Length: 471
Ligand code: HEM
Ligand SMILES: CC(C)[C@](O)(c1ccc2cc(OC(F)F)c(OC(F)F)cc2c1)c1c[nH]nn1
Image (cartoon, rainbow, N blue to C red):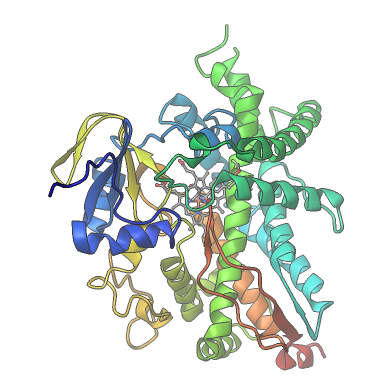
């Protein structure tokens, strides 16, 4: 009695549980490196820190391209910008200029810390008007970190109640929704098998996004002074200037669509991800009041109420720095990075990997590795401190929240500051507690282009100690 023909097989149900954890459950059967084939496209999944560091660092440039996706093609205006562009001059140029702009914000009145502490102060007043109420702090934080990103790109910020802030939130919410139904890792190309409006809806929100950035770029051309370089849009237009003296090879790379999409990748990435981490950290502090207490005690002991937090306070506020590290471990912004692609025939762990092969780092597996992490499913900021509690450690090498190699986060500095500063300023001012209905946020989360958390509310009272310190 024979056996049936078999035209296809998959090791686990599609659209059942989260992708990254399904790949990770799978290492028990098939190991830390294994592949899957859809027609002609082939995808490798890496889930051990050593092989991941080979893809990202040692052979970093070999695996530094990005794969063509129909949904990502739109959000990037056909693979322009940075995050979703293939390895090339465009990507190399724009990524370089983008980083050069962050250099401008080391010193002065445009000192990055000053810009942040500024928009954080407005945030804290805004939140104090809700003393005694339970609220969803998504939008107030969204506006804070939009203004920072907007000051670095434009030297502009949105005044309060501006209706554009609600427009931006809308198309951001729309891009996130149609860009993926899970992480950017669909085994099955569902949107080509069945008819659907997914791409049509996406174009709408990107169209709004693109038209809006376009207005801003036209208005700025009058205002541009070659002698005044203080934001990203300057760095980009200066580049276009120095190229067209006829034009250089760099000229075709700095058209207004290439400049537009670059800003849109800075904005799109920076804002929604920084906001998500803030929501994720409060989520964890509401589940772990014991950690919350030691964080209040630490910040009262080392900063007080005579002044506001400063980057300088990073050296004394250690448990806070560890808590941010432990949230980015348990809940990586990008539990599977962005897909890398093999630019050239190569090898991972001495296995052959053909040109054009989608390679995926399963960061979720690196951060939950039983052997590399003690009690990996637990929230223990202690694990990033010596047993004393007096300086920070790197307890494991299987920890790359911002990735590594040629394709790592370019806004790592900015995020590490914002996340520290925001969280300091709030813990100083505010008591943060479970609302009166008694509901706690769900830490399960929601994988999209960003690893998001279900919306949740928090009761917020100004702190006893902070009041009495005003006389
Ligand atoms: C806690 C905050 C953040 C985390 C954990 C994070 C993490 C990451 C990761 C894992 C990648 C991809 C790594 C890879 O594909 O190899 C990435 C890419 C990127 N991030 Fe972030 N990121 C954060 C915040 C930001 C911020 C605030 C910005 C603001 C500009 C930003 C801009 C970018 C860009 C432009 C890329 C694409 C780089 C490229 O493809 O060359 N990120 N980030
Ligand atoms: C891990 C990575 C996928 C990402 O989450 C990321 C990167 C670029 C994004 C660009 C967006 O704008 C437009 F191009 F689609 C975007 O749209 C929406 F959020 F508004 C979301 C984006 C998310 C990220 C974030 N930080 N570092 N990497």
